[PDB]
Image (spheres, helix red, strand yellow):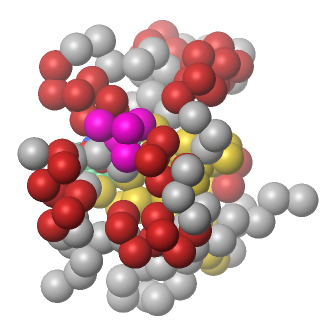
Amino acid sequence: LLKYNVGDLVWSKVSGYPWWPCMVSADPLLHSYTKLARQYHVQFFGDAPERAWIFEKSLVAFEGEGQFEKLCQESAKQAPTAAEKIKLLAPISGKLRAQWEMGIVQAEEAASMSVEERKAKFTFLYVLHLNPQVAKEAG
Ligand SMILES: Cc1ccc(CN2CCCCC2)cc1-c1noc(C)c1-c1ccc2c(c1)OCC(=O)N2
């Protein structure tokens, strides 16, 4: 039923990290955004930009920050060991929490923008660099 496209907003669950706001985008070298068990190429929102391929089973549509609590809770049932379960919590403090909060601010802005608007603003530029307007607003 679900098939993501470039510009779609998703929470991504990665080993060693809590659910993080992302945007589906095209891989700069392969030129694809999906491949086959299905994978999608995503950008991680925040001030320290990263990209990666994620499996669909580890993506959930992004609506807003309010979803995080239920994602943390529901994922606990499928993370039986302590090191996995502890990573579901929002980062305690420091630089990782500030990155996650900035990620959420950016994703919430993207969510009230159109697909093309969020793509023009938030897509990374490749030579991987942030769009200068995004970098200035983040600091
Ligand atoms: C895919 C990936 C690649 C590399 C690095 C390491 N990199 C993190 C940023 C600082 C330098 C070291 C982390 C991930 C990653 N895998 O799962 C999540 C979640 C992340 C991630 C964590 C934090 C941030 C991020 C992605 O991008 C946006 C941001 O501002 N911070």
82 relative to 8, above or below: above
Over which residues does the magenta segment extend? 102-106
Task: Identify the residue at image location x=48%, y=70%.
Answer: 117
Query: Closest to the observer: 114 or 39?
Result: 114
Query: Closest to the observer: 136 or 55?
Result: 136
Query: Closest to the observer: 74 or 5?
Result: 5
Tell me, yes or no, if residue 70 can be seen here.
yes
* Residue 46 placement: quadrant: top left
Query: Closest to the observer: 112 or 84?
Result: 112
* Residue 63 placement: quadrant: top right
Q: Position of residue 29 (x, y in %)?
A: 36, 88
Q: Position of residue 110 (x, y in %)?
A: 48, 53
Q: Main secondary structure of the magenta part?
A: helix
Q: Position of residue 39 (x, y in %)?
A: 61, 65
Q: Position of residue 64 (x, y in %)?
A: 57, 35
Name the side, left or right, on which 27 lies relative to 63: left
115 relative to 113, above or below: below
Tell me, yes or no, if residue 79 can be seen here.
no
Name the side, left or right, on which 75 lies relative to 95: right
